[PDB]
Amino acid sequence: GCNKALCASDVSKCLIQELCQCRPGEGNCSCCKECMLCLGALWDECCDCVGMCNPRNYSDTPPTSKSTVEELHEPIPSLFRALTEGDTQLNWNIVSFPVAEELHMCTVVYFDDCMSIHQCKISCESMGASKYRWFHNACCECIGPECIDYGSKTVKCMNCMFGT
Amino acid sequence: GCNKALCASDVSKCLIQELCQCRPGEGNCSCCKECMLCLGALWDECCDCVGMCNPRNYSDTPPTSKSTVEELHEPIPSLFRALTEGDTQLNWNIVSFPVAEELHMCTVVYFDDCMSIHQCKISCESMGASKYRWFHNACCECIGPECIDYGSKTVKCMNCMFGT
Ligand SMILES: [Pt+2]
Ligand SMILES: [Pt+2]
Ligand SMILES: [Pt+2]
Ligand SMILES: [Pt+2]
Ligand SMILES: [Pt+2]
Ligand SMILES: [Pt+2]
Ligand SMILES: [Pt+2]
Ligand SMILES: [Pt+2]
């Protein structure tokens, strides 16, 4: 967790000054701003040692955790509904879930085969979608006009489950 | 707009069949699914010609339009409040706006100097922020525990206005 070699000098200096005596983890941390100021430039790499921030990660972050979301110019809701309601394309998996679950109803389209972001944007634009979310596993999720937000964080598209 | 050389053959073939006779732009487009099926693989690059999708872009998309958003593991709201309420760091610009404006109140932090995404994530994590949004102009916006969503789409951080 703590990087002792980098941080021991300055961290001790703050401790001697008696800063960073307050734990954020339970209750208010009155001293947190003062502790950050005393650490200065080393706060990012040494806040773990004083307990003010989480230890340097013990875990490997899944690629799916990142996603990049953009809102398409000039959405065409009628096209999106027309291509969604009817017998959906096999390459397309269609999910409708109640709107604001991710935080009437929100409908999204999950492309099957994994695709590049630029392709994902083009395909959503051709679909009339209001917005698209591109998972960094490369799964593509067009977002419908109804949806308030960017839709489900889940990588629900078949034939690209990588990251699970 | 329309790519005549690529699309003229197939597009004419659909037109002769009398598909793509319905405009999505005003009113329902009954034929939209049939038109897409007739186009098949060329729908993405030729839907403009039949009017079912917007013409290939006349405009250069600003870099700021893309952003990538991730939610930090183990957020520490007390730290975020402690470092936000008090005399804010000069490198940090602090904006509080009513929650759900982007779609009680949502508070976000806009880093001044433009930074890489990995740095932006580390700095937000040290800040206790629930989530971070990284603009592709490279402006970094940590997102507070209060905020329902990912916060303002605006690139409001000083000393990285590139893309405006
Ligand atoms: Pt700091
Ligand atoms: Pt429902
Ligand atoms: Pt399947
Ligand atoms: Pt799966
Ligand atoms: Pt299609
Ligand atoms: Pt307010
Ligand atoms: Pt400024
Ligand atoms: Pt500006």
Image (cartoon, coloured by chain):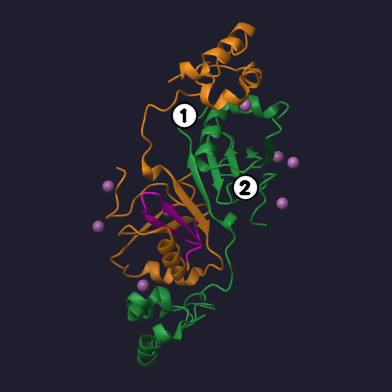
Chain colours: A green, B orange
Q: B8 and A160: which one is in front? A: B8
- The answer to whether B33 appears left or right of B115 in the picture is right
Mark earlier in primary sequence (1, 2): 1
Residue holding disc 2: A152
Pointer 1 chain = A
Task: Indicate the position of residue B105 as horizontal and vertical percent values.
Answer: 46, 55
Residue holding disc 1: A74
Q: Quadrant of the N terminus of chain B?
A: top left
Task: Indicate the position of residue A41 as horizontal and vertical percent values.
Answer: 33, 75
- The answer to whether A57 appears left or right of B62 in the picture is right
Cβ of mark 2 under 8 Å from ligand 2: the answer is no
Task: Indicate the position of residue A82 as horizontal and vertical percent values.
Answer: 64, 24
Give, as a single range, the part of the protein colored magenta: B129-147
Amino acid type indicated by mark 2: Ser
Q: A8 and B95: which one is in front? A: A8
Q: Residue at x 44, y 62 (%)?
A: B118
Q: Is residue B150 above or below residue B23?
A: below
Q: Secondary structure at mark 2?
A: loop
Q: Are marks 1 and 2 in contact (CB under 8 Å)?
A: no
